[PDB]
Length: 375
Ligand SMILES: Nc1ncnc2c1ncn2[C@@H]1O[C@H](CSCC[C@H](N)C(=O)O)[C@@H](O)[C@H]1O
Ligand SMILES: [Ca+2]
Ligand code: NA
Ligand code: NA
Image (cartoon, rainbow, N blue to C red; front, side, top):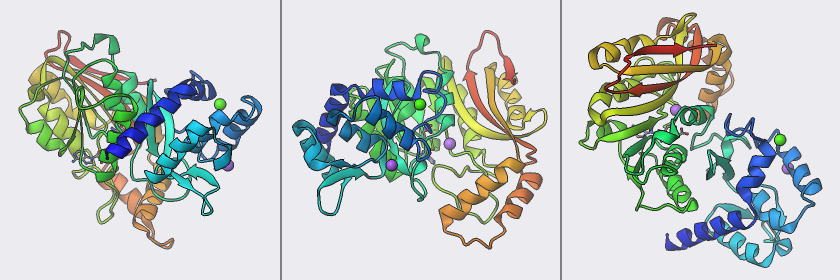
């Protein structure tokens, strides 16, 4: 607890000493850095290792860094003296592993990335290995943040990142404002955002971390200038269990998006803005949910902009959904989940397509209206 805080401080010192963020940015390059967190994965790790070995010369100062980035083993005695004591502290914290004979250090369940200028530990199981992850991050996380107008954020603006997960959106907002609230209800994400807050030299002085249900924060009396939320939004067929980060509420998975949008006229200060993201079902003309938002244009004079950045036919999602459901619940391979998914997509969701959509909503707009951007 204080030992962990000191360990994260020393980790931060190591990342600074060897220029981690710059090395990550160089490896992935500027045309990929903000596209997706799934850049260093089990399918690219061999190439990452080759770069460290052949272009960075295998320098020992980068050995602990690779343990964190890909899980690659480093011989304990080969670590530089300062990095060796940090490695021991990370093993004690459960953030790296030691081999059974203690002669090397290697990856545990946390992967070190950089996103939007922040250093971030994420759940390594999303990009490596074969066990279902407990903390989500994905391209939807990134595209939510991409559309934020950072130059319009004042130091005194009050911002909230609901359903914060790893903390990425809250930490991004903390680059610009000194008043950030980050919320979640999962034990595992809450422990991780606490680590990532400290990893970026923040504390409760400028970023509050709160265990609180989305609808409780939304009903509350606190008012915000800026809101971000990537909520659970996936609709799974009746009878199937997902995970805390994936399964949306309501008949079509969008209950949490409805909850948020409905309270924006009250929770945002006049002229404040919210950024949401979801993979929205729709027909050939667009996502069904945008039709529900005309009530916010007419009823509350908001401006609402929807940025559609990925389109897939519903049939292309049947496999990924069924695979996720099978793996999350440990179901056997003879269950016809795919037919259940198809039937649900067509009766309940009316989903011909899925549209990965970032939505910007502004209260008290001078130019109210709904705008849907498609390529
Ligand atoms: N009712 C609820 N109230 C608050 N958080 C919730 C919630 N239900 C699920 N969550 C949290 O919602 C998150 C959705 S995943 C989004 C994580 C992060 N904001 C990102 O963009 O990458 C998960 O971390 C999950 O624990
Ligand atoms: Ca590369
Ligand atoms: Na490897
Ligand atoms: Na989500």
